[PDB]
Amino acid sequence: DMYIERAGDITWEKDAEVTGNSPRLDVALDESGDFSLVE
Amino acid sequence: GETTDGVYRVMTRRLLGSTQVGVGVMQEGVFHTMWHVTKGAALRSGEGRLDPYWGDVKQDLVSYCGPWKLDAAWDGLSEVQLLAVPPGERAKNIQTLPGIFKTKDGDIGAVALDYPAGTSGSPILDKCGRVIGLYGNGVVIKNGSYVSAITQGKRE
Ligand SMILES: CC(=O)Nc1cccc(C(=O)Nc2ccc3c(c2)CNC3)n1
């Protein structure tokens, strides 16, 4: 049996840690909701 | 049950100890999470109970108590914030510029941040604080890192 616990407010944080790149990927989505890389 | 708006952890006591299997958004009395977190199962909120209302395995989304309420979209140009809620750790905002998933049915925003599977359902926000989608469904690229889609539902 699953349960929920509050973890915080949904707010934009100014001066947050800026990381991660922006890749343009060719993907496919199957009937089971799973993404896969088209190459 | 607690129905205050905000981000919530999705926990379970079926395995060893208490394990975080995912995260979700409470908004307008509706709990929104990813399908692979709950598999459509009922949730508990203190003494109260939340029952599934809408779900779709292909979109990988589910709503509890009512229809999907989140409808903000990524503008295609601006940086966004993953409000990551990792297992055993405090909620933290990470800013990133999203990439693109190019599909046969159009393009979807994608965040290239690597977090544990128990972080699935964490909201991705715009500069206004609006939820533009949830984190936790994507693909694994050559280098081994995760690239998640910015998965948004439809508001009827
Ligand atoms: C290193 C790594 O893999 N990490 C993360 C991070 C978030 C999510 C997942 C994941 O596995 N997402 C997931 C699982 C099951 C399903 C779907 C998405 C949609 N169909 C069912 N992995």
Image (cartoon, coloured by chain):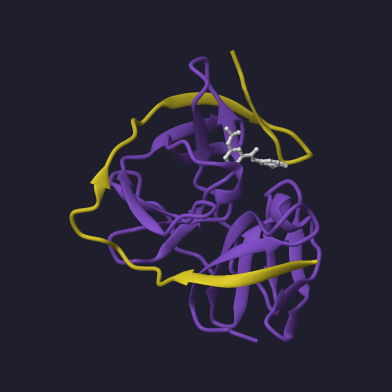
Chain colours: A yellow, B purple
* Frontmost residue, B102 versus B56: B56
- Tell me the quarter of the image containing the C terminus of chain B: bottom right
Count of all numbered marks drawn on residues in the image: 0
Residue B119 visible in this rendered orientation of the protein: yes
Is B9 on the left-hand or right-hand side of B13? left
- Furthest residue in direction left, as rendered: A15
Q: Is residue A35 above or below residue A17?
A: above
**In the rendering, at what x and y percent does residue B50 appear?**
73, 78
- Left or right: B118 as drawn, with respect to B132: right
Who's the residue at 60% across and 62% down the image?
A: B154
- Position in image of residue B76 (x %, y %): 35, 44
Image location of residue B100, percent across then percent down? 44, 34
> Which quadrant of the view contains residue B116?
top right
Pick the quarter of the image with the N terminus of chain B. Answer: bottom right
Residue under the image location 42 percent in, 26 percent down? A24
Q: Name the residue nearer the viewer: B91 or B106.
A: B91
Above or below, B112 relative to B93: above
Residue at 55 percent of width and 50 percent of height:
B119
Ligand 1 quarter of the rendering: top right
Q: In this rendering, would B132 be left or right of B38?
A: left
Residue B69 visible in the snapshot: no
Q: Residue furthest front?
A: B17
Q: Position of residue B149 (x, y in %)?
A: 52, 41
